[PDB]
Image 1 (cartoon, helix red, strand yellow):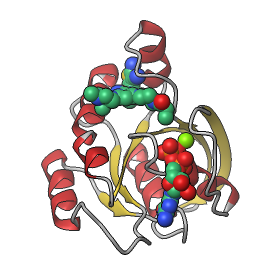
Image 2: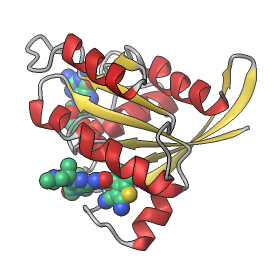
Image 3: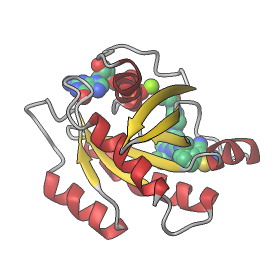
Image 4: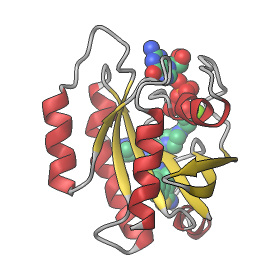
Amino acid sequence: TEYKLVVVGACGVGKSALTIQLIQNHFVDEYDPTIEDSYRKQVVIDGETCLLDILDTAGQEEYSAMRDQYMRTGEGFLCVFAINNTKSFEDIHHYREQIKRVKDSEDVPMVLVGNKSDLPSRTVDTKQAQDLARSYGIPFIETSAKTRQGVDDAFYTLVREIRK
Ligand SMILES: */C=C\C(=O)N1CCN(c2cc(-c3noc([C@@]4(C)CCCc5sc(N)c(C#N)c54)n3)nc(N3CCN(C)C[C@@H]3C)c2)CC1
Ligand SMILES: Nc1nc2c(ncn2[C@@H]2O[C@H](COP(=O)(O)OP(=O)(O)O)[C@@H](O)[C@H]2O)c(=O)[nH]1
Ligand SMILES: [Mg+2]
């Protein structure tokens, strides 16, 4: 069963590192910030043999029909910010609104992801992020691509939401 997932958020939050942890089970601390591609992973989720097709976004900020059609292929979206970057969290509402527009839906499967949870000096609090996820009616997952904390929780929760 195929699930088309899209990982979005400001560049530098760890979209690539999270995707590589899921696919390859290791931390890649350096990955060209301009590389945008789809990566496939066969995994078992709640007994179902899944094919995850994950689009790790980069590109340009472009509101063309071509880019909208490309993003519209996504079934579920991980909206990622970094816990030590207030700007990336403030940007979440823009990503949520563009997803809602291209999918033409108020309940697109989404998970709010607070990455870099291994770091000791945060600027965005768990309470404010939990509250934003509550405003959207979506789950909030704390992750670390460095340690693998929350990686399956984020992706598998998104699959469960698509499956529902
Ligand atoms: C690291 C790579 C890089 O240089 N960039 C440039 C900045 N950039 C970017 C993209 C977006 C943005 N807004 O929506 C999207 C997605 C990818 C989200 C899913 C749905 C759709 S439909 C569609 N078309 C697009 C696109 N593009 C999307 N990406 N926003 C921003 N900014 C930064 C400036 N700020 C005032 C507004 C917004 C938060 C930047 C791409 C990565
Ligand atoms: N400490 C820490 N650094 C991370 C984590 N995820 C990514 N990084 C770092 O954050 C930067 C951006 O990562 P990258 O995967 O390129 O993010 P992207 O631009 O969103 O694809 C790099 O310096 C990574 O080493 C994480 O969970 N913890
Ligand atoms: Mg990247």
